[PDB]
Image: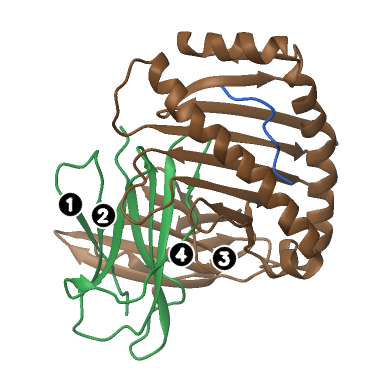
Amino acid sequence: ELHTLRYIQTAMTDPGPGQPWFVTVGYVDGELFVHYNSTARRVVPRTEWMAANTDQQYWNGQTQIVQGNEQIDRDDLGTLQRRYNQTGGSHTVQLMYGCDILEDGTIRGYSQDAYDGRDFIAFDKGTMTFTAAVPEAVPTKRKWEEGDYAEGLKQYLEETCVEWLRRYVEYGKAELGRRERPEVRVWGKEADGILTLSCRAHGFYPRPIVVSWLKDGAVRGQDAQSGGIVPNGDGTYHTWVTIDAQPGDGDKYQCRVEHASLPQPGLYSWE
Amino acid sequence: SWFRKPMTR
Amino acid sequence: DLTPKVQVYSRFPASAGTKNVLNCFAAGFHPPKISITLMKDGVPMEGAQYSDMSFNDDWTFQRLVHADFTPSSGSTYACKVEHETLKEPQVYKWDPEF
């Protein structure tokens, strides 16, 4: 079974109006479970399974781990501006790290950093060295290698990350492993001698879905336009696939929805 | 659990 | 290059008089500073909730704005998006499909 843990960090100089400068969130199998912002200054759960399983000791302890990271990113925003020779303006520091438990049992650990949307420092678990993408990343590479900070980071991605992710999966066993059926609606619009058939799926879980258009029982790929898998505010997902067809052929077209919740692929039409 | 950064850039 | 790709949709299939949630999702944008507003007949839609900001592997940001609403016939629902990459504010109309 595939299980992933991802922690993303964002430090901004221009949030801007009525928004926190430091935002950081966590993900268990692509689902939002933990949140922290520079305004509230407290780690708040985002799922019911997270709050019901953890005590006050954990929530108070996690806040200080992030509070320290907030201070580090505050100093780094000023330190990096001096290296690039910048007086002010809009600048963003992004950090992405976590561990993935693959289907074949292999554990993959990653830690990447960026400045203004461009790669800065990428951790290599094999060679135990921090890779520099830009010439301004060399002083960070030199500093992090002498102090042997790579050993503590390797200990986290291989041990601390895996142990906690395995616990979070156990806490939300019924929530993460649930099957939610999508509500499918088919609507056609005729304009300039073109019939546009839209197939929309509402509120499904998990995230993977295969929505394909069929004409006379045969699948039509290249003509179909999709908007990908977009999320909902309650943890569910949404998707839309549109196809351009000749007017008077609408009845020949059928939308096929392939999802884990449905035992057999559901066939829908404009009716 | 979040990783505690042991050093500044 | 880094312009936000915006999609306007409802949580449940739209029906006149039935309670629903109007979602506005913008993705693939940088810098993170963005102004996403849900509008009913060219005016903001009261109490709108802003979800926790996220970014993918390519460092491009994404944000979802959702608000509880009751769709009515003869009313136009749209989403106003303002960003540094866009020269003029972009308005995306919601297709009720009913």
Q: In this view, does A229 lie to the left or right of C91?
A: right
Chain letter for green, please: C
Q: How many labels does the image show?
A: 4
**Are discs 4 and 2 located on one and the same chain?**
no
Q: Residue at x 51, y 20 (%)?
A: A120
Q: Does residue C4 sit above or below C73 in this rendering?
A: above
Mark whose residue sits in front, 2 or 3 = 2
Where A230 sits versus C84, above or below?
below
* Chain that bears disc 2: C
Q: Position of residue A256 (x, y in %)?
A: 53, 61
Q: Which amino acid does label 4 sit on?
A: Gln
| Residue A156 at x, y percent in the picture | 78, 33
Q: Distance from label 1 to label 4 (Cα)? A: 37 Å
Calculate the distance from the C-alpha at mark 2 to the C-alpha at mark 3: 23 Å
Q: Nearer the viewer, mark 1 or mark 4?
A: 1
- Tell me which label, 1 or 2, sits earlier in the chain: 2
Q: Which amino acid does label 3 sit on?
A: Thr
Q: Give the residue pinned by disc 2.
A: C81
Neighbour tally class for label 4: few under 14, some 14-19, many 20 plus, Cα within 10 Å:
many
Residue under the image location 77 percent in, 70 percent down: A52
Choose top left, top right, bottom left or bottom right for residue A60. bottom right
Chain for colour blue:
B
Estimate the spatial distance between the alpha carbons at disc 4 and disc 3, rounded to whole Å. Answer: 24 Å
Residue A237 percent coordinates (x, y): 53, 62
Q: Is residue A44 visible?
A: yes
Question: Label 1 amino acid?
Answer: Pro
- Residue at 56%, 40% (x, y): give it: A70
Q: In this view, does A120 lie to the left or right of A33?
A: left
Q: Are marks 1 and 2 in contact (CB under 8 Å)?
A: yes
Q: Colour of chain A?
A: brown
Q: Mark 4 or mark 3, which is nearer to you?
A: 3
